[PDB]
Image (cartoon, rainbow, N blue to C red):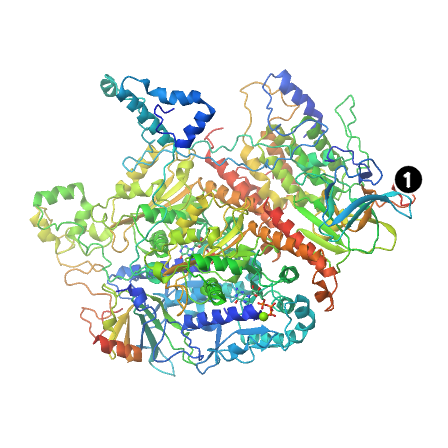
């Protein structure tokens, strides 16, 4: 029900007048409203209702995908899982080094969390039993202990510095690769292979 | 139709002797003609179906193409006289897996072909009048592993003289057949 | 994984000497028969093994025979550019033509050529080890393409049976035909072909005329422009047998997933994109629109409006730069469309196919170098309108017994005409009942 | 353990509809039409449980913040805006699987082969209409009729709840089970589908009738028990569903005993009869299907 | 200027090479040599390695690597100017020694430098 | 000690197994030429479960590849880590199933199953103590379903007491490759319920959703999905190959997840899975792993757990973690979502901790959900199957090869009663 005859087409209202001059004489007299702003609001309402009658149209019918070199072979390739990465997790630096971080901070950081503290102190260790072994088993523990004010009882476990055969730390260690002690440049020594 | 009918040992769908024999049948004639005349050897009125193309002129049992009559009678019997022309007829059946099969008997073919929907077999006739028993159940059991349940429609083609086409439940003999169903 | 092709008729031979040129251009085999040594295209041997056979001396001969009755179309194959490509025994020519007579080429003339053609194809297949299945070419409106084109198929069926046979036939147009007796040959060939071939792809000359005039912008499309698209279609539907792909399909997939019932094997080919060099690069070709461009009736190789019918099953072959994600995305949106529809009993009727190698452009051709293309092969109930009209125009002639004296006078009788008529009527009823 | 399964049909139905006063379930009469004409066969299936729950938008959304599932925030509407004093009201201010119904009744439209073969009229069935519970007047003698063609027909008619059909089907099943001798064994593979279909529907009376019929089927034979053991995979699930359903009265006496309404003991008796009949390697399959069952020595 | 994939669509680099493979205890030999033909496509910079299928060798021969862009152990993909004759190329933890190049490849590198 | 024999059926199984073998080889440090080059001794003690040191530091997978199209094995041999497979394990036919379950189960089964059985028997008797076989295949095609199910059954009567894993993908409605998908799927799931010890439900639709939304990938080809599946399998099998604070092997998980023998279909999820740009900005603690693990949208199948109840569940943790965080998080999960766990089974979660995280990661997890919501997928497949079967569509392609409509009937009936028992076990109170 539009107040203004503007919305209707030409021959539509022409046929209406040919059929019924009755509605044909309201759609002109519908503008009898004194306030033009009110009639404009009603026109806005009828236009809005007509727009609501119409349905929305999506603008993404044709999907467009960027291609690196426009070849199916290239696009369908997935890179092979080839990594020379170190197997130990402790070798990677997931946190700030414990050395520079403040002593009391390291102390209460241990107090809330022993585990990752033990891992940071023992970068080479990989199993839980190795990391939570002892503060006296690893010779490198003592600098950390007396830097962070952790008392170390004497003779723990033994006076002779040793007893970590699995983990390669200090002077007790050898790479599983064929040129043990490292530096393999030929096939004769192994070239860092098995 | 025919679902509320008694469907006794005999059931006639078309008889050439009546006011409006082709009352349920739908006529489809082109390049042909249909008549009701009396023949010279049984002294009775028969219906005429002749067409230049056998596949063009025919009559189907149910007038409405969507609507199908249901007859459970195993045997279908037709009385036709051989004119030494091409003639054929087609019958649809329903099995227990609820699918529609078709059996078409043709006078002008030799091979017998079995297909999921249409089974065509050759059929021979003598010189004069003869009656034919179809035995729908046996054909359904032979061509397919299914069995006979319902017959949906029957349609006869051109170049034939049909009279008293009817269904039956047994292979009735000459003596025990009722008076109105014999040939002479 | 090797396939051999047999070409029957003057149209079959003309299609063959446009598909084999494309095959030679696809693997770099020069018309002399040997690949160049100074430079190579592509990589990976045994790609040509499905079409060519190597003699051990750097030679490649096609696995095809050109079969015809008139010795006038094979000669320019014997004297053309590809003189040395085809083995001389492969090209088979008769002495007298059947002259647009199905009965003549089926019974009188064809009986003297079928035996030696079978003898040749036997030892062609003997060289093969993993024969996938034969594929044929013929025009059912013609004479030799129908008579012996059906006799040879019957003898192949009785000789092998389980081997697949693909039929790429060119049916007569509804209104544009070059003969007057083509309905008779079409009916008498379709009746016998109805139970022998396993795959029967329809083709129409004037539909290809329309698509070439519109998409390719050619005001005078001749036969060479026609059969150059069928070559692309055949290459696309066999491209998975040669080159590797993410998602490949062989002929067995086609038979299993495009034949819902034994006698319902009649496919409506399509292709996309059919573009010219001028408009090829300005348009940003992508999977969505080319898949959409493959379903409108204005691009179907046969003028059979699929809007009237329903798709029981559809097949797709993607070549070039296509990933398995956008194909599924496009299939979803197409399924959400309402202009087309699928049959009730089949919820999913798509057999997708993804390959890697883009279609190869032929020099001096109509198409351009396109980075990805789609070759769609559907199966819709709309194809009942084709036989419904061809049968009517056949009955129009058969009512007067016109031209039957040429067939019957050869030595046949009138009964098989009527049995072919009723077989076509039964096919019409079968196509009608499956759409319920 | 009932002498006649059909001897309590009408009495139980009448008691339920009138004497007890409970509302009788009156459903699945859509499309039945009138009498003297065939029922319009609906393509619906009784056995299939076409629930297919569709929780389009009332599905709660998983919260990664707090592990508890939460419902999505309500859509703000323009009808309800922010009032003057609601600000102080704000200061002064649980998901579950929807149904997954397994014990609800499954619909069973009257589309069995029994019904069709009945309005067709090829069945030699008549009602004696005697003073006692009605028998069946057999037009042809029972011993000579073909069991392979008729037995699957009647077991498929057990599913009927319509008054004139279920009684005839049950009584025919009873009559051939009592009369048949050694000719039930070759046809027993064909009887799995109707029994399974009748068991799949969650109707109390239907389950009771089919359980009694199974008891008399396994009982009234010679070695049919050893042939039902491989088919335990398609019959025992309903037994598992309803094994423990039984009424408990603290010290009251169960009056509804002359009629076998409670299927809890019926399932136990059927499982036992399975155990003794064909007991060679029979406990393994039943225990595999029903884990709570115990050996009857 | 035209897109790369159409400028050189069929231009293919083709090199001849080999890589030794230490075979284990056998009266026949103590080490074997596997001839390989390396294909590089100028279109999309995709590699390809295949064997020439010696006649009486019991090794299963044929294609060696899918024709796809290979990535080196450290990073960025291969480049046409890294296939000199007489140099060692490292692909997938293997070292092929390029021995001879095709005439097309020879003239292409000569134009390149 | 414990050994896992790997079998792949169909082309999809071949790429899945290839990705699994590449990721496992990279985990154990062996290069594409089959030689060890790692730095940790932990990559040596338990490599016998997957590899056999032949001679001169050559490790070959204990895998048998099975297919019916030569292109598949040409691809798997040509691809990277393709020369590590022993050629004798390439048992193979010639013709091809052609997406026909009937063909791959009857017509090519009787000719090819002898050689696959021979080679798998030889491989099994080669090692000392079998832990169990692992089979990867698809439920859509013919050779993946028909051949694989028959092989699984034959191994079942040959080795009844040995474990059996089955990683099988199922067809999805939104991602439908072929037309006969329900026909093969119903028969395959019919064969799987009695033979396989348990099956893990996978599909390409859920993988696509996960890689679209979580990974935020632009072009996720099959490589990414196969990598996800391979990582899932590696996380599943990690407890066999590495030390941990709490161990849980295949048999432990099987006995802790299966309450009744017919309930052996599980939904699986993996975590963490973060975008490339967002990987550096987020931390590694148990709560973040748990939050993504239990998300209903993170499951790798089209079976929403929100529609059902959780019967049992597992959380296999890899990395240097705290057990207290583990069990308190799982307790919180159980308590907050008290209505989505079955009532008559308290403590519906089994947990385990492994000390070896995957390469490049600090923490990892793997979820095994035995929820009764898979009946949704089963009904979804069954409705399509019966829609096609009611009109006998495409039936001649199976009937003419030896089958009967009977087989389809018991297939749909057993699917129906399996769904019925799932419905039974979903809503059943502690007391009746
Ligand atoms: N698409 C296409 N159709 C062709 C071509 N040449 C002929 N045809 C079709 O073939 C029909 C003529 O029959 P032929 O192909 O010659 O087959 P035939 O029956 O053996 O006729 P003859 O060769 O003369 O014995 C025409 O109606 C055309 O529709 C062609 O080059 N391309
Ligand atoms: N995840 C994954 N799925 C695949 C892969 N290749 C194919 N598929 C799926 O497997 C289904 C088809 O399996 P199919 O090829 O018929 O297996 P077949 O029995 O061996 O022939 C399709 O729906 C694909 O989604 C792949 O490399 N990875
Ligand atoms: Mg010609």
* Residue in the image at 14% along x and 43% along y: A109
Mark 1 burial class by Cα count in 10 Å: few <14, some 14-19, many 20+: few
Residue A165: % across, % down = 21, 60
* Disc 1 CB within 8 Å of nearest ligand 1 atom: no
* Residue in the image at 31% along x and 51% along y: F218
| In front of the other: C241 or F342 | C241
Q: Chain of mark 1?
A: B
| In front of the other: F110 or F154 | F110
Residue A156: % across, % down = 14, 52
Looking at the rendered image, the quarter that the N terminus of chain F falls into is bottom left
Q: Mark 1: which secondary structure?
A: helix
Query: Is F329 situated left or right of B67 in this image?
Result: left
Answer with the quarter of the image where residue E103 lies: bottom left
Residue marked by disc 1: B179
Residue D38: % across, % down = 70, 32
| In front of the other: E39 or B179 | B179
Residue A66: % across, % down = 30, 54
Give above or below for D219 relative to F353.
above
- Let me know if residue F158 appears in the view: no
Give above or below for D69 relative to C312.
above
Query: Is F98 situated left or right of F87 in this image?
Result: right
The quarter of the image that holds ligand 3 is bottom right
Number of marks drawn: 1
Query: Is D137 situated left or right of A8 in this image?
Result: right
Give above or below for F375 relative to F94.
above
- Let me know if residue C395 appears in the view: yes
| In front of the other: D206 or C57 | C57
């Amino acid at each position: 029900g539009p107040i203004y005859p503007s919305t209707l087409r030409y021959k539509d209202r022409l046929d209406c007048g040919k059929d019924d001059a009755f509605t044909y004489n309201r759609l002109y007299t519908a503008t009898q409203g004194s306030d033009v702003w009110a009639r404009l609001t009603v026109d806005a309402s009828v236009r809005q209702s007509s727009a609501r009658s119409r349905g929305s149209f999506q603008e993404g019918q044709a999907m467009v995908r960027h291609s690196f070199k426009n070849s199916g072979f290239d696009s369908n390739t997935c890179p092979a899982v080839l990594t020379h990465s170190t197997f130990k997790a402790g070798l990677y630096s997931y946190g700030v080094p414990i050395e520079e971080q403040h002593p009391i901070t390291a102390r209460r950081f241990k107090q809330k969390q022993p585990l990752e503290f033990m891992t940071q102190i023992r970068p080479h260790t990989e199993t839980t039993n190795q990391a939570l072994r002892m503060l006296g088993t690893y010779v490198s523990d003592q600098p950390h202990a007396d830097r962070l004010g952790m008392f170390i009882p004497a003779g723990c476990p033994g006076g002779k510095p040793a007893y970590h055969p699995d983990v390669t730390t200090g002077g007790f260690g050898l790479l599983p690769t064929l040129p043990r002690r490292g530096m393999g440049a030929t096939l004769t020594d192994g070239r860092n292979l098995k | 139709m025919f679902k509320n009918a008694f469907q006794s040992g005999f059931l006639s769908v078309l008889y050439s002797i009546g006011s409006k024999p082709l009352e349920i049948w739908d006529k489809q004639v082109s390049n042909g003609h249909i008549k009701r005349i009396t023949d010279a050897d049984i002294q009775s009125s028969v219906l005429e179906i002749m067409g230049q193309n056998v596949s063009t002129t025919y009559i189907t049992c149910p007038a409405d193409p969507n609507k199908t009559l249901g007859i459970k009678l195993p045997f279908l019997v037709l009385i036709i006289k051989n004119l030494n022309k091409y003639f054929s007829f087609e019958v649809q059946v329903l099995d227990d897996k609820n699918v529609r099969r078709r059996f078409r008997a043709s006078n002008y073919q030799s091979t017998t072909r079995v297909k999921p929907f249409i089974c065509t077999m050759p059929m021979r006739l003598d010189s004069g009048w003869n009656q034919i028993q179809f035995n729908l159940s046996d054909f359904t059991r032979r061509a397919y592993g299914t069995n006979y349940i319902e017959t949906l429609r029957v349609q006869v083609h051109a170049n034939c003289r049909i009279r008293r086409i009817y269904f039956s439940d047994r292979l009735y003999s000459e003596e025990e057949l009722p008076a109105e169903f014999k040939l002479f | 994984r090797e396939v051999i092709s047999i070409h029957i008729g003057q149209a079959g031979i003309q299609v063959g000497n446009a598909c084999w040129e494309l095959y030679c251009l696809e693997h770099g085999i020069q018309p002399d028969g040997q690949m160049p040594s100074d430079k190579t295209i592509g990589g990976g041997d045994d790609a040509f093994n499905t079409f060519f056979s190597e003699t051990g001396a750097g030679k490649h001969v096609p696995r095809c025979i050109f079969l015809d009755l008139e010795p006038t179309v094979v000669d320019e194959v014997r004297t053309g550019t590809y003189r040395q490509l085809f083995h001389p025994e492969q090209l088979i020519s008769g002495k007298e033509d059947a002259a647009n007579n199905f009965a003549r080429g089926h019974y009188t003339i064809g009986k003297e050529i079928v035996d030696l053609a079978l003898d040749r194809i036997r030892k062609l297949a003997d060289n093969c080890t993993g024969l996938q299945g034969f594929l044929v070419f013929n025009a059912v409106g013609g004479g030799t393409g129908s008579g012996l084109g059906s006799l040879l198929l019957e003898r192949l069926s009785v000789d092998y049976g389980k081997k697949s046979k693909l039929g790429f036939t060119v049916y007569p147009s509804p209104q544009v035909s070059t003969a007057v007796v083509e309905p008779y040959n079409s009916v008498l060939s379709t009746h016998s072909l109805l139970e022998h071939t396993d795959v029967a792809v329809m083709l129409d000359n004037e539909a290809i005329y329309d698509i070439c005039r519109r998409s390719l912008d050619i005001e005078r499309p001749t036969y060479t422009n026609l059969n150059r698209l069928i070559a692309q279609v055949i290459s696309s539907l066999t491209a998975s047998l040669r080159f590797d792909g993410a998602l490949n399909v062989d002929i067995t997939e086609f038979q299993t997933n495009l034949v819902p019932y034994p006698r319902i094997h009649f496919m409506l080919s399509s292709y996309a994109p059919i573009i010219s060099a001028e408009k090829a690069y300005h348009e940003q070709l992508s999977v969505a629109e080319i898949t959409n461009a493959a379903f409108e009736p204005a691009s179907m190789m046969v003028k059979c409006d699929p809007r009237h019918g329903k798709y029981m099953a559809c097949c797709l072959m993607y070549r070039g730069d296509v990933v398995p994600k956008d194909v599924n995305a496009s299939v979803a949106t197409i399924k959400t469309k309402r202009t087309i529809q699928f049959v009730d009993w089949c919820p999913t009727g798509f057999k997708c196919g993804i390959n890697y190698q883009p279609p190869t452009v032929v020099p001096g051709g109509d198409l351009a170098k396109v980075q990805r293309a789609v070759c769609m092969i559907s199966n819709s109930t709309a194809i009942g309108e084709i036989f419904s009209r061809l049968d009517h125009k056949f009955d129009l002639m058969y009512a007067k017994r016109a031209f039957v004296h040429w067939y019957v006078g050869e030595g046949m009788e009138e009964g098989e005409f009527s049995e072919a008529r009723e077989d076509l009527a039964a096919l019409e009823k079968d196509f009608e009942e499956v759409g319920a | 353990m009932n002498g006649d399964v059909a001897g309590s049909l009408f009495t139980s139905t009448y008691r339920n509809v009138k004497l007890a006063g409970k509302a009788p379930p009156a459903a699945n009469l859509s499309g039945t039409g009138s009498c003297f004409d065939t029922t319009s066969l609906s393509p619906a299936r009784a056995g299939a449980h076409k629930a297919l729950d569709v929780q389009k938008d009332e599905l709660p959304v998983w919260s990664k913040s707090t592990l508890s599932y939460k419902y999505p925030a309500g859509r703000p509407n323009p009808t309800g805006f922010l009032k003057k004093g609601d600000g102080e009201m704000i200061k002064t201010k649980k998901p579950s699987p929807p149904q997954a119904g397994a014990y609800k009744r499954r619909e069973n439209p009257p589309n069995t082969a029994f019904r069709r073969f009945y309005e067709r009229g090829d069945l030699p069935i008549a009602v004696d209409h005697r003073g006692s519970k009605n028998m069946i007047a057999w037009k042809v003698d029972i011993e000579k009729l073909d069991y392979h063609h008729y037995l699957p027909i009647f077991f498929d008619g057990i599913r009927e709840t319509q008054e004139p059909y279920r009684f005839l089907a049950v009584k025919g099943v009873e009559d051939m089970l009592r009369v048949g001798g050694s000719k039930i064994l070759p046809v027993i593979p064909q009887l799995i589908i109707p029994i399974k279909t009748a068991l799949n529907t969650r109707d109390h009376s239907v389950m009771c009738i089919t359980l009694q019929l199974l008891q008399k089927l396994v009982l009234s034979a010679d070695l049919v028990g050893e042939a039902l053991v491989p088919y335990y995979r398609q019959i025992l699930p309903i037994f598992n569903l309803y094994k423990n359903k039984n009424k408990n009265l603290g010290d009251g006496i169960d009056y509804g005993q002359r009629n076998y309404d409670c299927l809890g003991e019926l399932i136990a008796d059927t499982l036992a009869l399975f155990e003794q009949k064909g007991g060679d390697d029979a406990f393994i399959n039943i225990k595999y299907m029903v884990p709570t069952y115990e050996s009857s020595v | 200027k035209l897109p790369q994939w159409v400028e050189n669509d069929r231009k293919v680099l083709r090199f001849y090479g080999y890589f030794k493979e230490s075979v284990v205890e056998s009266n026949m030999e103590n080490h074997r040599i596997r001839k390989v033909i390396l294909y590089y496509y100028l279109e999309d910079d995709s590699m390809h390695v295949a064997e020439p299928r010696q006649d009486n060798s019991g090794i299963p021969q044929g294609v060696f690597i899918k024709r796809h862009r290979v990535t080196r152990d450290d990073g960025s993909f291969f480049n046409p100017g890294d296939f000199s004759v007489g140099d060692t190329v490292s692909i997938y933890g293997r070292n092929f020694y390029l021995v001879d190049a095709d005439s097309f490849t020879r003239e292409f590198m000569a134009a390149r430098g | 000690m414990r050994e896992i024999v790997h079998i792949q059926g169909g082309q999809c199984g071949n790429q899945i197994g290839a990705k699994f073998w590449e990721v496992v080889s990279d985990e154990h440090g062996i290069d594409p030429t089959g030689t060890y080059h790692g730095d940790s001794d932990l990559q040596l003690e338990r490599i016998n479960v997957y590899f056999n040191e032949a001679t001169g530091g050559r490790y070959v997978p204990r895998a048998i590849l099975m297919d019916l199209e030569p292109g598949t094995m040409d691809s798997v041999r040509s691809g990277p880590y393709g020369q590590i497979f022993r050629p004798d394990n390439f048992v193979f036919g010639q013709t091809g199933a052609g997406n026909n379950w009937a063909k791959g189960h009857y017509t090519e089964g009787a000719e090819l199953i002898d050689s696959v059985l021979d080679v798998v028997r030889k491989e099994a008797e080669s090692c000392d103590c079998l832990q169990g076989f692992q089979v990867c295949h698809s439920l859509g095609g013919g050779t993946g379903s028909g051949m694989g199910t028959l092989l699984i059954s034959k191994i079942r009567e040959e080795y009844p007491d040995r474990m059996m894993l089955t990683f099988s993908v199922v067809p999805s409605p939104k991602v439908s490759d072929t037309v006969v998908e329900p026909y093969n799927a119903t028969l395959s799931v019919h064969q799987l319920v009695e033979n396989a010890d348990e099956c893990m439900v996978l599909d390409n639709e859920a993988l696509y959703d996960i890689c679209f939304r979580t990974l935020k990938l632009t072009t996720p080809t099959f490589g990414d999905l196969n990598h996800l599946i391979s990582a899932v399998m590696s996380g599943i099998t990690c407890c066999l190959r590495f030390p941990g604070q709490l161990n849980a092997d295949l048999r432990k998980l099987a006995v802790n997840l299966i309450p009744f023998p017919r309930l052996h279909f599980f939904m699986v999820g993996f975590t963490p899975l973060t975008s490339r740009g967002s990987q550096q900005y987020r931390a590694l603690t148990v709560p973040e792993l748990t939050q993504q693990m239990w998300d209903a949208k993170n499951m790798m199948c089209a079976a929403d757990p929100r529609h059902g109840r959780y019967l049992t569940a597992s959380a296999l943790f890899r990395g240097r973690m705290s057990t207290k965080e583990v069990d308190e998080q799982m307790l919180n999960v159980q308590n907050k979502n008290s209505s989505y766990f079955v009532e008559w089974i308290p403590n519906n979660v089994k947990s385990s901790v492994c000390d070896i995280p995957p390469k490049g990661l600090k923490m990892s997890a793997t979820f095994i959900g035995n929820s009764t919501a898979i009946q949704e997928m089963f009904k979804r497949v069954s409705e399509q199957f019966t829609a096609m079967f009611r009109r006998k569509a495409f039936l001649h392609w199976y009937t003419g090869e030896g089958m009967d409509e009977m087989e389809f009937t018991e297939a749909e009936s057993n699917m129906n009663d399996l769904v019925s028992e799932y419905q039974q076990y979903q809503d059943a109170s502690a007391e009746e």
